[PDB]
Amino acid sequence: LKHLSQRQYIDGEWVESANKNTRDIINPYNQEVIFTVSEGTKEDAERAILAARRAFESGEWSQETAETRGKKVRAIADKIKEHREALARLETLDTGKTLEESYADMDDIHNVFMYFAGLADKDGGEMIDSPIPDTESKIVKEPVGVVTQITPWNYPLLQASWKIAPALATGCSLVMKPSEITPLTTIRVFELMEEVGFPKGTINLILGAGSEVGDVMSGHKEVDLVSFTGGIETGKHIMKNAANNVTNIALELGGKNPNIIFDDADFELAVDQALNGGYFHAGQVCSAGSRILVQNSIKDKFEQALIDRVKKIKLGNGFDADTEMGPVISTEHRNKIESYMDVAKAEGATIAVGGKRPDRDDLKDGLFFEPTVITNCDTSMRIVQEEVFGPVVTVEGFETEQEAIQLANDSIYGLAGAVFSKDIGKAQRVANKLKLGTVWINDFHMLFAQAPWGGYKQSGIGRELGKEGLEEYLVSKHILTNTNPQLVNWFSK
Amino acid sequence: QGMELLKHLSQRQYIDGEWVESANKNTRDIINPYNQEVIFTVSEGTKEDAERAILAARRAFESGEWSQETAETRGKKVRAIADKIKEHREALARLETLDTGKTLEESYADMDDIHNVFMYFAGLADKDGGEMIDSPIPDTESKIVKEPVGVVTQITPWNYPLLQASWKIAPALATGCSLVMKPSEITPLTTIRVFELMEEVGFPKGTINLILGAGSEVGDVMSGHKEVDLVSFTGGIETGKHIMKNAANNVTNIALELGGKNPNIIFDDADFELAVDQALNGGYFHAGQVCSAGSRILVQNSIKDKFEQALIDRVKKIKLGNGFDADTEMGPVISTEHRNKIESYMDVAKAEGATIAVGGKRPDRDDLKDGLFFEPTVITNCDTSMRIVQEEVFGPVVTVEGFETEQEAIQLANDSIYGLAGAVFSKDIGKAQRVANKLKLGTVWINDFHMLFAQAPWGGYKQSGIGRELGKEGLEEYLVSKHILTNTNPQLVNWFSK
Amino acid sequence: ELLKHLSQRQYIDGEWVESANKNTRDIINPYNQEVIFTVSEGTKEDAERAILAARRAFESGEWSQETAETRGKKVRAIADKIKEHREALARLETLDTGKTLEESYADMDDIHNVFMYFAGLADKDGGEMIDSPIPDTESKIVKEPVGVVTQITPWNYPLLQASWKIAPALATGCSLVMKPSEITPLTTIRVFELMEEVGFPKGTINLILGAGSEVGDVMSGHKEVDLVSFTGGIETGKHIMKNAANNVTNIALELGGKNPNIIFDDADFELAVDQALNGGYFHAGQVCSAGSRILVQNSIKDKFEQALIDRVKKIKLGNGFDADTEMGPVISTEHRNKIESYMDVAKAEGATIAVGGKRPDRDDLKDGLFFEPTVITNCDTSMRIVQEEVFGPVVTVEGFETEQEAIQLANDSIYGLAGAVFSKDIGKAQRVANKLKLGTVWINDFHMLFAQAPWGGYKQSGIGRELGKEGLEEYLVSKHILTNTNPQLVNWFSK
Amino acid sequence: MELLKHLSQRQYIDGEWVESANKNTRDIINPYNQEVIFTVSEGTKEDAERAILAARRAFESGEWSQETAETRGKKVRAIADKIKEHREALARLETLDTGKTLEESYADMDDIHNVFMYFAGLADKDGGEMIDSPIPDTESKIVKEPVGVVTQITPWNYPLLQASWKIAPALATGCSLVMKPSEITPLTTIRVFELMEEVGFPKGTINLILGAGSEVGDVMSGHKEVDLVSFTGGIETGKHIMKNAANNVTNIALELGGKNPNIIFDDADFELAVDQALNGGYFHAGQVCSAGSRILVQNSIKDKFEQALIDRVKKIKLGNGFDADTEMGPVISTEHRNKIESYMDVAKAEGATIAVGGKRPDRDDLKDGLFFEPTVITNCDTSMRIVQEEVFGPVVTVEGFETEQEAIQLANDSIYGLAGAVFSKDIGKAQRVANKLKLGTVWINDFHMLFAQAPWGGYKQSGIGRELGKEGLEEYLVSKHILTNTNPQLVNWFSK
Ligand SMILES: NC(=O)c1ccc[n+]([C@@H]2O[C@H](COP(=O)([O-])OP(=O)(O)OC[C@H]3O[C@@H](n4cnc5c(N)ncnc54)[C@H](O)[C@@H]3O)[C@@H](O)[C@H]2O)c1
Ligand code: NA
Ligand code: NA
Ligand code: NA
Ligand code: NA
């Protein structure tokens, strides 16, 4: 932290906020202030957007060869790997998740940049067989333009990489703003990108409250695409604001992801994966398997096994090797999780285990919340329908394959889910009917740069990762040339 | 005139496999803009009718009867629609001309295009179910399956009713979606007729639905209902924005096409007479009521005076009249409200200091007195700061601005909130290509105007829209990607203590 | 009655013409060995004239520069004619080739779908725009029709195989010269009549009738040919490829196979028996996709052999026009003799002819080219009867112990066209499918193929593909057009 | 020279550097002075067979063929980085072995780095397609797998460049390969094998055979365990290879040179056209598959063009590829120079004019090398052997044409179809012409431009298939349709 920048990065320069305001960043493990950064203004955000537009129109990045753009994106990928240790530590300090989880993030981030580096020069568009004689028809794919990018606090650098990599690869200019409470890795990646070298204005980092600078990032006339990952309420607000300029939006908003366990699942595998689904990063994951659906014939056996394991989950400091689950991100977020416990009980569900702050001494100063299992609930309940985004799972039974599908689809969301069954034919039937962007068969949480990620229904609009993710950052232009032009002579001479 | 067509035309909405009146029995009189006479009367539906249609589309979608039909068979049905369009080409063209005022010849060209749109998408239906991914994780299979997006609402404008409908209906049916369509309340005739033809082909109950009525009565239901997966709208910018904001309530995908301020760039080395011809075509086809209209002429200074004179002299000869008469070159505008809007723009142009060089009023001639006619108009001595240059008038009106250099042409052409289409005229093809590469437009024509077709995507940069219609990209609006990842050798992670 | 109005001539450069030497050939019905029709037997000069006419038409641009959309519409019109004449075409095919009328109806439905598929694909490409690594350049790849193509088909599924070649050729804008098997030209003549009704520029389509040994070499070895597409046997295929090499001409070959039908002990047993029968005996095993090599898990091998043999004895032989017929005759005297000589080979190597292996004695079968459905047991991979394509109503049965051994045995042939895996354990069937060196692998099915997916062989089963986008791509050629938009002198060489 | 002290002299088979089975060797020559510079193993047909069988064994093991596509990409990228790291030494080796200028060799090495990088990036970007099946209750997918065992044979003009075009996609897709460079120019290929060994590939995945095409070539093209033969060279050897591959119905990818037209209209930028006619004709002494050996010039400017070209041809600086002022080095071998010389006799006997050059240069410092003067042949026509046949030397012919139509007819009037250019300031016209030339690559107002992002290959007798681009990678893939019936039912056709 001694050498980490504390400033925004606008138009090739590290700069303070226009009003000199600052914000203290906290470690959720002990609620101690660990760093202080600039808290930018809406005029700073506007200046970044105007700089991105100017850089885009200069052509220095947008007209660079795709091959060269790919080489630069690859150079970022290499810096991530080179600084893997320090990045992982920063991420754990800022977000609370285990160091091992943070190492896995850094390995993935390297692969994300590498994937897009390699995709950069592989399209360009299509030649069309024109239906009009004596014409040439082609579709050229250009960078979409100036893009704003807003990320959440759970996986700051990972989510940032999903946006930055395709934007740079395609030739866009970008303005990024990480969550105000978790900016450290994002500042660091900007330092690394500056070392690679990009024309002035091509990349910009704004630091600040979503409520202060967010609307300018979603509502400015010079933006061609707003790409946001976070919660549903902010997402909807952002889309409404983007509508003022008919601006493209790419949204990923979390989910109510079903984890469907059939009676012919590998039982110990399913228990393992129900734990993974529920409690990695204290359930603060877009992909969290918060809604367990278990076949009735094994429901009691399953609940007992799960509960017994949940009691053994090891809570602690993300830097300690024995820690299995760290704290949740903030006081506000822990309070929200606590109020959901009251909701669940008032609706008549059972808090089978957990449901409170742990009492242990070394956990007292941190934002800890016990891994929790909620039983005796049904699809009509708020605790089942709503994304708690904490270390909490619900358990519902189902009788038949048809019922599992109906229940799993009975939410406003559609991001991801899993089916556990040794009968692969059955798992595939079920997968084909789930209205989800990603379905895992005998697995959980698996995602990678090669394949698109995103939501049906209220889980989002568009995709990130894969060729489809890159396509958000492109725009099609049909250039039609009449090679033997003739007068139409419709209007009198 | 047009008579016999209407004798057997349905007057009702089509919901869940039945032709039905409005829930409140309300009706609306449809007008011919040539003479402002009532030509037909149709049901004016309610918001509950729209909701019932949406719920019927959802039920049909979940039944799987269309959404799980083979893509090959779906293509065959979309092809059968295409064949019915061609079979009824004459009656459809006549209806369209009766309802919208444009010339019969223009309507025939629409019907040919509509046939080709359905045929294109019929052929595309079974050509792409997704991808196999080379997974980075050993012992996994990764595949991307493309499914129909789901239930789609489709809202069309009054200028090219059936054409715009076909751009939405064809890919929706080809992919296996269920749909609810609502044409403009003032021009529903061809859309009713195409629903009759689709019914003849045969689609499961609830797969297709037609709502008739005011956007202000049923529009919000169509854009804001939780059971909709995609709202596809073609029309004006204000309504588009409102629709997008409403769709946000359910994070619903939107596909918008909203018109433009399309530049027609004429260099001093253009084929002069060609450029004059195409400036006229750009400006005045369908009385300029076209998303692709070339309303903003940018002409190189060295030939600007010559160009203005030639264009003005031609504009005075444009033949106004009944769309059914063979000599007619330009029909009336669509409604009293729209003519009034065009008129108020003339006042704006003069107040900001532009010159109405020719036209700018209603014609006096006797056979035109009863119709919604407005003279083809040329506005000169204007600049990019003016409202008359920046805003879409959507009437038989063009502005003319000069430019000195290639760079200036590009800067001016890009200086608008829009980005739908434009043209470059020059015999120096290398130059036209440079310019085309720099225009922020979804479509650029080199030595042509108004050319569009099913094979290529159409849509706007900036405020001209979101997404694309036509082409493979158009079909993709009606698809959704699902990543199915199978772990073929699953192992416990053993992260959490046992 | 069909035959009363059917043309007897070749179709060259827009005209129905006799052979240059007036020679003819009698066409036979294999059910009764009776002459049913007589057609021209063309010369090598006729073939050359067709090729030169195809070249001329191609260079005129009338088809090759027609819009892709309009080409598609014409291919679609052919598809509709096939359906319209479905009954007569099916009857002709059954008369000429001997297979059951029901099989022929299924062919005609498929043929309609092939033409329709390619009609729909015609205008869906054109090529790519490339993001060039050189500043101030535009790089595009335009896909053009390959050019003049020669097309040679076999006698088992004449029209079906013809459609696989004609449809993409016309869709892409090529000119073509087609020659069906000399012994089965009826439906191919008919389809040329139908194409003439649709209307194509003169020289775009040509039909040569005659012996492969008389006109074949011209079709494969002429300098004006850009692609030779052949479906048939391995020996002719190799000969063709060697001849095509004289002009470095592209080749697309599909040469049959030794297709494994792998049955695990956890297969749905009755399904596997049913499909082993389908695999072995449809069209008297005269199918590129025939499942002639059964590999059955040792644990169920005796059970399987007994059940298969008992069913094989009930197979109903007869006239393809009779509804109760399950298997018709084989195609010719020469082919039946070849099948017979294989029986001698199998016995000399020590295999057992468990059932069949001879001509049936029954009276109504005496005059036709019948051969009994046959099962050969007690054999192994070293045997000629196992390694070689018999292309008759004959299957061999070998046992395997493990999954690994099934794969090893199945892949132990020179061929690589198609095969199946039968197992209720889908995971296992998929593992096996990934390791088989075959262009098509069926999991719990057999003989399934369709226009939407490419068909072709690894190893000695062929080169290239037919059907699907890949099938169309055989009839395209890529051209990279690179424009320097700001050309500068290099000034390497002294001024 | 110091380069050579540590360079391997052996073949690389099944993970080991090995000598020829019979200890035979071959002396490698520098064409600048005809001196022996190195001695390598001259392998036997049994060595080639052993390599092929090792490639097959490796392929079946799955260690490379089932490695993740992402990881295969990373390895191909590591090869790319080694090429750039060793750019200087590789360029010098290439110049020493082939005679071309050091500057040309540097450009090759830059291009080779980009080829490996391109294919590294493409490795994990496909996998196949999901098909919407026309049969209910079925799942249809096309999986793209490595084609299998591939044999790769390269020529002497751009040894490492041509090698990279084959190696990169083969490794990216998961194939096993056996490569054999031209017997007279093996140095950079040996070196690249050393570099690949440093990256690390499973045993048998890569193999290098060294030797005479006439001794080991037939095994490489005719062995039953080969799935693809990829050959770049001359037409006669290509045809022989294709005939041999036919014995096992083996896929072939051939690129065989051309008779590439350089079409110059009277509205071309004249000085640009002269510059590019020189580049087209004389880079690497015309020993280029892309050489613009057939100039077609509009009649109206033909005399002006000839005079301007001839005057420049006289100024071309011949010399040692290592000297900075050298513009054109020697041709590759005695046999090749003799072939070029016999073509001069042919041209004269047919009545063409040798307008300039047409002989060995007399100058002292050129006396010991395999030099041949840059040559312009005029007063010829399309019926002549000198016009129809690929000389592959520093020689161009010049023919006139009257109209656009005639330019096209003449340019297409050859057995070949690899590449060509159109020079005209009228871009509309250049595009019309380009659309009608039967060529795999057409340059508008440029020459010799090719790159990994776009496919390269020939119409007609210039080849079969493509190298470079996605289409190049596709030569190293094979499609398998896996069709699963998810609700199987008995057909019940045959009696029970
Ligand atoms: N892109 C085009 O082709 C196009 C078409 C028509 C109009 N325009 C432009 O838009 C301007 C306004 O045209 P307009 O107002 O006559 O048409 P509009 O933009 O309102 O679009 C008409 C369609 O939208 C429906 N609609 C109206 N309110 C709605 C709501 N709240 N929710 C859902 N649907 C609703 C209408 O009933 C009709 O079907 C014109 O002056 C012109 O500049 C462009
Ligand atoms: Na959504
Ligand atoms: Na937009
Ligand atoms: Na083969
Ligand atoms: Na060829």
Image (spheres, coloured by chain):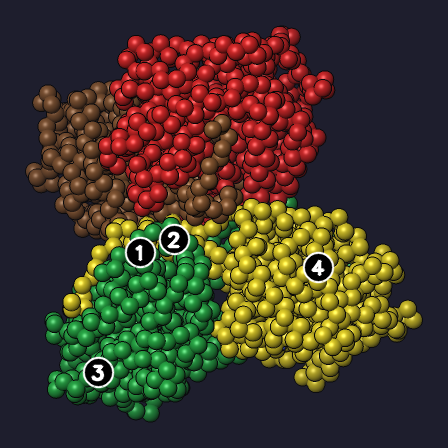
Chain colours: A green, B yellow, C red, D brown
Q: Disc 2, disc 4: CB below 8 Å?
A: no
Quadrant hosting residue C40: top right
Residue type at the position of mark 1: Asp
The disc placed on residue A264 is: 1
Residue type at the position of mark 3: Phe
Mark 2 surroundings: few (<14), some (14-19) or many (≥20) residues within 10 A: some
Q: Position of residue C127 (x, y in %)?
A: 49, 46
- In this rendering, is residue B150 above or below A247? above
Residue with the mark numbered 3: A368
Question: Position of A21 compared to D310: left or right?
Answer: left
The disc placed on residue B195 is: 4
Marks 2/3 same chain:
yes
Marks 2/4 same chain:
no
Residue type at the position of mark 4: Phe
Q: Position of residue B427 (x, y in %)?
A: 61, 53
Chain identifier of the residue bearing label 3 in the image:
A
Using the image as rendered, state which of residue A242 and residue A52 is in the foreground: A242
Give the position of the N terminus of chain B as an image quadrant.
bottom right
Mark 4 surroundings: few (<14), some (14-19) or many (≥20) residues within 10 A: many
Q: Earlier in the sequence, mark 1 or mark 2?
A: 1
Mark 1 surroundings: few (<14), some (14-19) or many (≥20) residues within 10 A: few
Please name the residue shown 63% across and 39% down the image: C76
Chain identifier of the residue bearing label 1 in the image:
A
Residue with the mark numbered 2: A426
Marks 4/3 same chain:
no
